Structures are given as C-alpha cells and as structure tokens.
Length: 321
Image 1 (cartoon, rainbow, N blue to C red):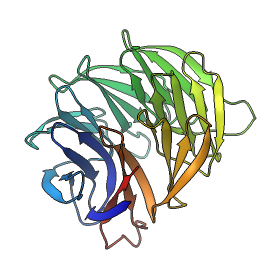
Image 2: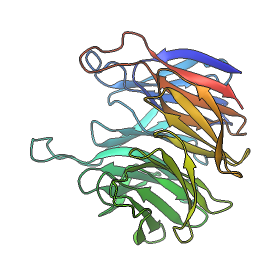
Image 3: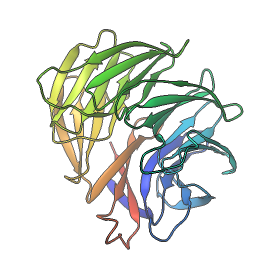
Image 4: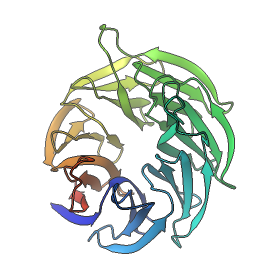
C-alpha cells in the first residue's frame, strides 16, 4: 500500500506530530528562481497540503520538539536555524550559527542534521566543514548555549539518547563520536572500521531500548549496527550505498534510502538482513515515521542538476508498513 503525492520543489526532511495529526516537509523550492523556501503541513493520510509556510531562508533539515510542539529547521545555505510553532505555523525566530563571509578561503560551517532533546528543550545541530562542530541551542529563546568543537571532517550524522544523556555524531574520518550532554564533552572517538579504506558515515539512527545504532556509509555497501555502549560492531548488513536511515521500535526494523538506486530497503533488526525493498524513484532523500510506527514517509526528489533543473515538484511517498 503506497501513495505518491506531489508537494513542491526541493524536498528534504520531515517531522511528524500526533497531537497536530500532521506531517511537515521542508522544501528549498527552485534553486534558480526562488529565494527562501516553504515548509508544508500535510495530511498524514492523503498527503494533501493543509498549510504552506513561506520562509525567508530555505529549510533543509528538520526535527520537532514534541513537548513544546515546536518545529526546528536547518538553513543549510545560510548557516542558520529556524523555529516554527507547529500548532499555528508561525515562524518564531531564527538564529545565525556562523555569520562569516562565504569567501573562497573562508567557508562558513553549515547545518546538516538537527535533533531536539524534549527533556531539556535543547536543540543540537551538526555544523559541517573541514573541522565540524555541533551547535547547542536553547529552544526556549532560540539563543546559542555553546558549540561542541572538533567533531572531525564532515560530521554530518546526529542522533540523541535523551534519557542516557548521550549525543552521537558520525563523520568522514570513519569515526563514531560519543558526547555527554550533561557537559557537552566528547567522551570518545571510535574508528568503527580498520580496513585501510575510506569510510564516510553519513547518518545514524538509534534503538535506545537495546542500545544499538544503525549507521550508513556513503563509501561502502554495508550498513553498520553498533553497540553504543562500547562501539563494537553488532552486525554488518549487506545493502547498496545507503544514505538516510531510520530505526522503527514498533517493528524492530530499520529503513534505508538508496538515492542513486531509487529504492528504500527494510532491514529486519532481529535477523540483521534486508527483507524487503520499496520502489521509490527517482531519488529518495529523507524518511519519517508516523508516531505509531505504522506508516513510513519518504521524500523523493526528481532527477535534477544545476544545469537542467527539474520542472516537476518533488513527492512524498506514504507507505503503510
């Protein structure tokens, strides 16, 4: 059971709220003709647009603080973060994370992934560059608390274990970095693999109940399952180049996107192998689950290049699991 619905150009990440009974999708819109972007509120079943929130800055990454029902979006090309009230769709404010000039020599860090700790109303944002950082933002006033330095090259991945007070990030140096959220200190940097090959761990999704992490690698066709207590490999699941990953507690499965391939794989987290594949052409980007874990949403981008931009809008695919 699948439903494909067109929404808008430049689709990226999504967030879901059971209380609002809604799914939101960040879209950057047209790269050549649009300044700023749009966050769309969609019906969880029909995927029809119920609200279009125009934004001065293009939104990319997305997350929601469930306790405050506040959406947080990463403004990747403006080194900023935006907060939007979920109930009203009102942009509450923004925070510039790196205000430096984008000169040929100076490259401002740009936000990638965002995660919100509902227990402390703190938002963590991975800022990527040659020397990455993790910005820690006060969700109560949209002001910076501090910045966790030295997370390595292109430390894109970000996942939070609120109860355990642990934050995890993964980078292009083949490391899994564990951070104590009580004091924002890096507790350890673990080289997951040692085969003399380059490993770029792009995303990470946690199974906090069993203390496991699912990590994708853009360089190898192998999804890693790691014990977050010590960093040991629990399993190496065979699967084509994976980018996005999302673990589903309700079904003990993990979903992974294959952008170039145009598919989404379902990994049985008990047997540790791929048991099903969904056809999601052309280029699947991000994933989101309904609160009950019974429905998977996939943002899918049309084939496009900054030479021949797509004329058709991107879609969101609803998959009844």
